[PDB]
Image (cartoon, rainbow over all chains, first blue to last red; front, side, top):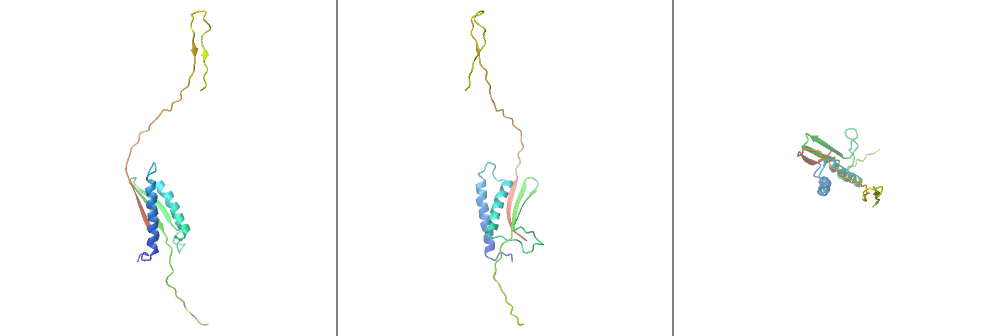
Length: 104
Length: 51
């Protein structure tokens, strides 16, 4: 029970991963090569495009979580190890509906 | 391209010698190098679902 048995949730992440792979392949031909600074600008652009398309939405509870749809952060431990992570809030589907009749 | 020669002899009344001078400037880009130390590392990429 991971919100993954819904069809579209893996589909968004697979599309984003494919786009990232294509970006990283092209970035390797740059003079510097793969760099943490370089990997953030492109990811921000693609995630903004995905937000514009309507795939990513703001969290349901604004008090608990921030209003931003995605969070992209870079962390450094020592100097040899870097880490780039992005989180996403997928769009929901409407599949169960209930109606409750009453009588005045 | 600009060329102009200057005379350097008062006359041939002493030694019978002809001299002419020219001035030039040379522009050179000297290189200076700063020594460095190289180390290796790794970068990892992960995708996550919020909350």
